[PDB]
Amino acid sequence: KGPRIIVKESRIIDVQGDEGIILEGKEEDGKIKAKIIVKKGYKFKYPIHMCFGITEENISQIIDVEIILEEDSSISLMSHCSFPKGKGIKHIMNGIIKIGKNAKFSYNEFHYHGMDGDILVKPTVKVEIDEGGIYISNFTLTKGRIGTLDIEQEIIAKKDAIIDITTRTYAIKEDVVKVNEVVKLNGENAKCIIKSRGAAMDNSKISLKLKIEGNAPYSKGHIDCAEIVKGNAEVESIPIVVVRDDKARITHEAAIGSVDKKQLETLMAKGLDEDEATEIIVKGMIGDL
Amino acid sequence: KGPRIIVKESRIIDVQGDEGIILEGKEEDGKIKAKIIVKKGYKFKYPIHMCFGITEENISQIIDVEIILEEDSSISLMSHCSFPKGKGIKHIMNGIIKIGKNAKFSYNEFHYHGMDGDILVKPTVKVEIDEGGIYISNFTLTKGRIGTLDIEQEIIAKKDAIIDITTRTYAIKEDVVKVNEVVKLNGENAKCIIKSRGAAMDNSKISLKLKIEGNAPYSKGHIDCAEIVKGNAEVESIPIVVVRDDKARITHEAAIGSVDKKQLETLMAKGLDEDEATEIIVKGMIGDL
Amino acid sequence: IMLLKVEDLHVYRGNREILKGVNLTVEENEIHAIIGPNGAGKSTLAYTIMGISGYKPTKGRIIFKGVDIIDKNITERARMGMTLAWQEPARFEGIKVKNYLMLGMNEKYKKDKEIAEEKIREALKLVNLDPDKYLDRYVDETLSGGERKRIELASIICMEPDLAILDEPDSGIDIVSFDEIKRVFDYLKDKGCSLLVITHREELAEHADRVSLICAGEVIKSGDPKEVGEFYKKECGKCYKKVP
Amino acid sequence: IMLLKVEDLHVYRGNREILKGVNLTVEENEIHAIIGPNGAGKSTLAYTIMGISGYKPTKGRIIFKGVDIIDKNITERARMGMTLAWQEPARFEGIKVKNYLMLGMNEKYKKDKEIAEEKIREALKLVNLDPDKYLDRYVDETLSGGERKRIELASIICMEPDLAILDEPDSGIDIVSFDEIKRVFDYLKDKGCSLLVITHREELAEHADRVSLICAGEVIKSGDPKEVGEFYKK
Ligand code: SF4
């Protein structure tokens, strides 16, 4: 079966672990407390699974979680959130992650929502990377209504460390999206990439804030952003770069508005019209066919 | 001779005009007042000249200026500032500019400074563009010390309008640079380019803030930025893009830090050393040689 | 009735005149190759027939299948049997190779999924790619310049038009001899297509049925592949001016 | 004395080797071509001899003009009379074509303005570019790929080195025929230069004085082009 966590209607239902991996989960002051540890030298073949579900109305979830990676270790985990019929929902989670020497971690989260529109989603995450450590993360929200979304991330990294961050969303009706994330490169030869992708429709509005600080010799960083606008939706983006060292280098690029003209003309020359071609490009951007 | 305004020792020393253009100036309330009016349908073979010069201690000068450019007319404006002794001096100017239907305007500003760093320069301008009008602007500060520099621009544009803006700087010792520029594309088919280039060394500090708002059908914008860091210098940049129409598109590109490695190795493989190779790349980017 | 005719065509790019009254014809089931110095008219002629935005004539006519096409848009030109391949093709976020080759497919293959499935594997083997490692990859920035160009040639085979126009068909591919490309030209002609080919190489021009030389926006020579090829070697290979 | 000896050379990039136990040499006034399949280490040799960053001998030795060069950087190797031309050159913002061709110009021509300005006109006509169209243009992203690669070969003619390394000199040029390229190789050999050419063309390999075949990071066979190309073909 394998190592896992299960929560339903804001109650814990299951938690279990293999050898070399320790998992903990209990309820306290109406919140959920959870912990994960992997010991020195263990590398795991398969992800941990954590699952959340809400079929009811006026439910609230608050989770605090601590994750520890010891020397030479490797792990990954999946988050699944299903909110069918969801109305008056609040989902909030607070993460602390520590990555040891030469260790590797990856994180994925995927959301399924209905059409009833009364939802708040609010993850907050703080991460520390030691010598030679690897960090990867991905958030996807592209099925159903979003409602309201808030993302906060803070990353601090030492020498030879590597970071890779992705977010992908699709917004409709009166949905609201807020993204805020910061990376500090505080050791030699450290590097990062930050990516965002998506589309907006109807009356929806979106704001993106992305920051990299280059504080140490031989640091490297890249940011890239793309967003497609339809109807009477509104978009704002604010990427920030700071450099404090003679041997660092940082770069960024973005494009916001209607679809690219050379991609559109290329599909017209194969026998499609503008409404057929524009929808093929949007389905690519949001991760469909 | 040609249409001009000249100031030294905070006092107007000459103002002169020509057939089809009216120039005026006087001293009031501790400030210089000046006027430029261009008559309907006129176009000229030359630029108009502004001149400022200071050669003595503790001087402060304030200028308020208004420029009117009527239907189907054209001008170009040249301004020179020379400040060979830097002992505690203030230069402040406020501009109002109006361009009518199918009119063309261009502005150039040049600064020459000495070896002493106790200087403050503070230009502020608001611009109005009516249908089919053109606006060009250039600021250059690359010789001597800067001291403290602080620039503000606001531009509003109607249908079929064209805008482009350039700034170039080179900062040394304890120099301070700030720039703040915003463009609102409110008419149909309006276009703009914003560009900045520079280098920073020693204990210098740079902050750059650039904004485009795309509010109307078929409007287009691009922001392009590059900065070179040496020694103990610090750089911050914040580009902003906002779009509110189904048919607009805006793009941004930036690079901050050291010179590119393949460009540097290509010049050393021709027999130069790394300090000869770095200074050839910088003088191309800031347009010096 | 001729498949394509071009009559006294002139074209401008801003204040610059590029094409200066070219005349051309293409017959049914023919390969016709155009050669000459780069930038002197080669690619702008190919964009002007396909109707790509910003390429519009100031005088002259273009007639396809006996209809004058100056009013028709890119979708209307593509509906009646014309298609283009770019020198440097576009890159797509999130579109997979097996979705891309299906999109323009000829109406005789689209009617059965097994005929459509076999045609795509046949078309990938013809361009010396290995099907089962490429079908699931994205048509994005990860591919090299030679991989992206072999995928665009697999699309023309699958789409099977009446007229295909190719701009610099080997550009971006690292290849030791042109016999991979000549095999694809022979296959398209056996199915009954006509090809209009824009090139700088003589090795591909000597495989065509007719050759024409464009220089400074005008036709200089036209006729037999071998008589024009010898002039191209002898005169153009030592000329630095590139204007008569 | 020989120009170059490469002796017992081993190189790895990341986890594993790209060159292993390579042995090679080059004579004065010789054209020598290297051939072989893609990924056999051909470009990794060219970067390793010139000393580009991220390539270093893990074992073995390199000798140029009877002197060891593993202690020397790119500038010091270039001062001895060696140089490289990249397979896809770099672009420079705000530098003119006529200013770019004056960098590294040979100590014979560089001394006087007339002798240098005519050397630049001769070099541009020899690659089929009209000087009066190109001298005042910038070496930036507004040139096409074929124009930028012709300008880099006009730079090698102005430097006139003792040893030159070319990685695919025909790639990205809009050639009418290979007789455009062989005319440059004839011009350099007439002045006494020695050439190392890395190429995928049997048409240019036929023109070399000697040819060598490198496969999987080892030298297989070398000698007369008429033996080694026909041996390679099977
Ligand atoms: S020889 Fe004549 S046709 Fe050929 S490139 Fe020169 S000018 Fe053009």
Image: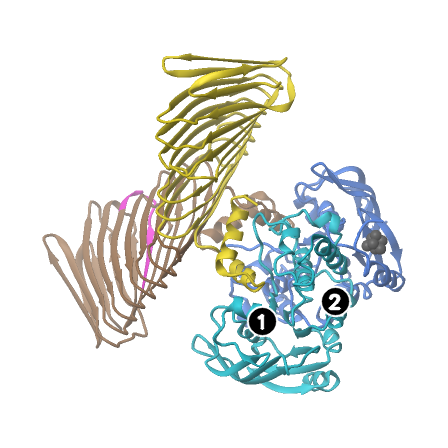
Chain colours: A brown, B yellow, C blue, D cyan
Which is nearer the N-term, disc 2 or disc 1? 1
User: Neighbour class for label 1 at 10 Å: few (<14), some, many (≥20)?
Assistant: some
The answer as to whether the residues below labels 2 and 1 share one chain is yes
Q: Characterize the magenta stretch by its predominant secondary structure.
A: strand
Magenta extent: A106-120
Residue A270 appears in the picture as rendered: no
The residue lying toward the viewer, choosing from D98 and D39, is: D98
Label 2 and label 1: CA atoms lie apart by 23 Å
Using the rendered view, name the quadrant where residue D6 is placed: bottom right
In the rendered image of this protein, does residue A134 appear above or below residue C82?
below
Look at 39% across and 17% down and name the residue there: B31
Hey, what amino acid is under mark 1? Met
Quadrant for ligand 1 reads: bottom right
Q: Is residue C234 left or right of residue C14?
A: right
Q: Identify the mark at residue D184; answer none if there is no mark.
A: 2
The residue lying toward the viewer, choosing from D144 and C123, is: D144
User: Neighbour class for label 2 at 10 Å: few (<14), some, many (≥20)?
Assistant: some
Residue A191: x percent and y percent? 37, 60
In the rendered image, residue A119 lying in the magenta stretch gets the answer: yes
Residue C236 appears in the picture as rendered: yes
What residue is disc 1 on?
D80
Q: Nearer the viewer, mark 2 or mark 1?
A: 1
In the rendered image, residue A169 lying in the magenta stretch gets the answer: no
Q: Identify the mark at residue A272; answer none if there is no mark.
A: none
Look at 20% across and 69% down and name the residue there: A37
Residue B68: x percent and y percent? 53, 17
Q: Is residue C27 left or right of residue A165?
A: right
What count of labels does the image hold? 2
In the rendered image of this protein, does residue D63 appear above or below residue D133?
below
Residue B200: x percent and y percent? 41, 47
